[PDB]
Amino acid sequence: IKDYPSNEDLHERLEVFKALTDNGRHITYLEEELADFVLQWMDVGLSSEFLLVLVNLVKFNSCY
């Protein structure tokens, strides 16, 4: 666990790596960077989970 980022700019992964790292995060920068890795598309067909985390967020949830 590090504040050291894990950012990438790749070509439509469409795999579970995001869902792999999408677990057990609670602190601010965790969710910040994690849902920064949202692809900002309109699609959900990959997975439709991670909903309670949304109702937990407030401001990131707003800009999200």
Image (spheres, rainbow, N blue to C red):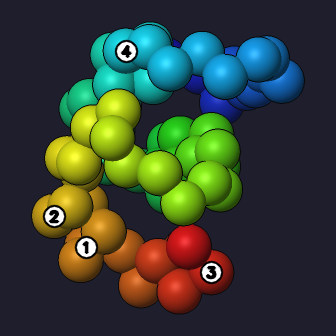
Front label number (4 vs 2): 4
* Image coords of residue 22 (percent x, y): 35, 31
Cα distance between the residues tagged 2 and 1? 6 Å
Earlier in the chain: of badge 1 and badge 3, it is: 1
Which SS class for mark 1? Answer: helix
Q: Mark 4 highlights which residue?
A: 16
Three-letter amino acid code at disc 3? Cys
* 16 versus 23 height, above or below: above
Percent position (x, y) of residue 38?
58, 47
Tell me the mark number nearer the camera, choosing from 4 and 1: 4
Residues packed near mark 2 inside 10 Å, few (<14), some (14 to 19) or many (20 plus):
few
User: Residues at badges 3 and 4 in contact (C-beta under 8 Å)?
Assistant: no
| Residue pictured at 66% horizontal, 30% vertical | 3
Identify the mark at residue 11; answer none if there is no mark.
none
Q: Which mark is on residue 63?
A: 3
- Is residue 4 in view? no
Q: Quadrant of residue 57?
A: bottom left
Residue at the spot of label 1: 56
Alpha carbon distance from label 2 to label 3 = 17 Å
Residue 52: which numbered mark, if any? 2
Residues under labels 4 and 2: Cα distance? Answer: 19 Å
Dot 4: element: loop
Looking at the image, residue 24 sits to the left or right of residue 63; the answer is left
Amino acid type at mark 2: Leu
How far apart in space, not on screen, are marks 3 and 4 (Cα)? Answer: 24 Å
Residue 15's image quarter?
top left
Left or right position of 3 against 44: right
Estimate the spatial distance between the alpha carbons at disc 4 and disc 1, rounded to whole Å: 23 Å
In-front residue for pair 6/63: 63
